[PDB]
Amino acid sequence: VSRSQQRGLRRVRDLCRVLQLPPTFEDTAVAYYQQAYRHSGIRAARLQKKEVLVGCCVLITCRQHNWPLTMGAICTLLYADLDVFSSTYMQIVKLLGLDVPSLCLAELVKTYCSSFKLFQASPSVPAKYVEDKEKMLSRTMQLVELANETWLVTGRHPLPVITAATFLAWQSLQPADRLSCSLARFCKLANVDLPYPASSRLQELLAVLLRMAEQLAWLRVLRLDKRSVVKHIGDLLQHRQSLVRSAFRDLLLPPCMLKSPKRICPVPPVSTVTGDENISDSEIEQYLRTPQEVRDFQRAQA
Amino acid sequence: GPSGIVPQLQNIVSTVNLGCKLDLKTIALRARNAEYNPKRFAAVIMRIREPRTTALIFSSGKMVCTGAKSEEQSRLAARKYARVVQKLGFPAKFLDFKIQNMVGSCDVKFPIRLEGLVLTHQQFSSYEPELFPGLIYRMIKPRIVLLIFVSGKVVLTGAKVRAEIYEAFENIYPILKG
DNA sequence: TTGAAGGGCTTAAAATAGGTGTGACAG
DNA sequence: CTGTCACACCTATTTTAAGCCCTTCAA
Ligand SMILES: [Mg+2]
């Protein structure tokens, strides 16, 4: 019956309709918001938390049905702070005692890759940049699965991985005419925002494909680089399972492990402290201002 | 069969009651190592060079000591802040000293499939890579929270005694290994 | 253009505490 | 229509982890 609860339930329904979700999703998300509101910790929360809670309840519903809604996308639609969304989501999952399924990368690849406006020519999309939607989706998914198998996805934001993989799939489908286009120019013509980590993900994925190329004698002899490896991506993906097992068999690790050279280990000092040693007057007096220091400070504040 | 890995203590949080009311303006004006911005935060921020630590001193006489690397260092530093406050003219006492929190860290030196760990140990695990790179593991015995990273680096926190950090690490090591 | 490098945030724990947001109570 | 009541939850302190995201600067 609460004015902020009524407003919240109405906002939950409006978010589901804006997102064009199946009809059953609305009811489930409304029930989660109601369940949340029964807890005193939620009832006494800031109106800003009650606003993002709308998004948490819809996201939980979408995660249970493998609907690939990202936390970033919800916060953009709700004009909400991601950090407030983060703390509210973690709280409500813990409070409702839920085992929320992880984001479905396979379904995100389909939805996100289809938003890239590269399927029809236009003044900003020339003929040689136009690609088949099915060929695009299939190769992007294979490159996302490769990134996941070669430790590039664990602990990272998942969307920039798909941005890097979509760009590489697009270039490898017509390498002669698409290697002059950078990641930034590609996102701009496809009309998609460029995620900040996407350039790092691209360089990691190119280095992984270069290590795989070392497992094939006829590719190893070509002394490939991050530019020349692109025309052989089709060939490498054809044998991705075999090439990955061969690369691990002969060091393939998460990028944060290989390597951290700038590290200091001699900073810790040996400790012989008991906590019971005498504390002399001279040891303490050094932390006190002198009568002159006090006067000079007082005059400067007057 | 121990791991042969000993977690390193990184930070100790302790509290003590100086048992008397304090004028924070007087402490800020007469100490050298005091930082006081009441419009920003209601307590004095005090620092000593040895043991290298920071104290939060409240007008109620209560104090929080942070940054020590051993429970002994935390006690010695807490006694030094109490002695600074006494020399400033207050009848400060050293009452109810208590270690409140301990943070440990170590490395198992092999990668961890966090996406797999969150499935096999779901009832203790939380892993949301859109929000944080590490898996949050809430162990019940001992009651310790561990942050587990893809690198094999582990952060242990919430301990009241050193043994709880060591116990939690010996418990998690076979889970991570197999 | 495109990177590196450095600062400051996210997550976990824990105490300290005033001021004030927030909603359901009594009166 | 106020007072009480019981929560939230901002500012801040420490410390590790790895990622993000921004400004800043270099050939
Ligand atoms: Mg906290």
Image: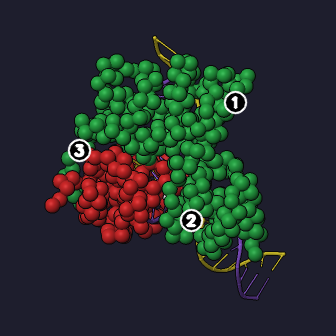
Chain colours: A green, B red, C purple, D yellow
Residue A92: mark: 2
Instruction: Say if A200 sits above or below B170 in the image.
Output: above
Q: Nearer the viewer, mark 3 or mark 2?
A: 2
Distance of mark 1 from mark 2, alpha carbons? 43 Å
Disc 3 or 2, which lies upstream in sequence? 2
Q: Are marks 1 and 2 in contact (CB under 8 Å)?
A: no
Relative side of A45 to A149, left or right: right
Labels 3 and 1 in the same subunit: yes
Question: Badge 2: how crowded within 10 Å, few (<14), some, or many (20+)?
Answer: many
Percent of width and height locating residue A18: 74, 53
Three-letter code, disc 3: Pro
Label 2 residue SS? helix
Instruction: Say if B143 sits above or below A273 in the image.
Output: below
Label 3 residue SS? loop
Q: Quadrant of the C terminus of chain A?
A: top right
Residue at 52%, 32% (x, y): give it: A169
Percent of width and height locating residue A91: 54, 63
Residue at 45%, 20% (x, y): give it: A227
Labels 3 and 2 in the same subunit: yes
Residue A120: mark: 1
Q: Could you say which is closer to the camera, residue B81 or residue A301?
A: B81
Q: Quadrant of the N terminus of chain A?
A: bottom right
Three-letter code, disc 2: Ile
Residue at 34%, 30% (x, y): give it: A211
Distance of mark 3 from mark 2, alpha carbons? 43 Å
Residue at 64%, 47% (x, y): give it: A73
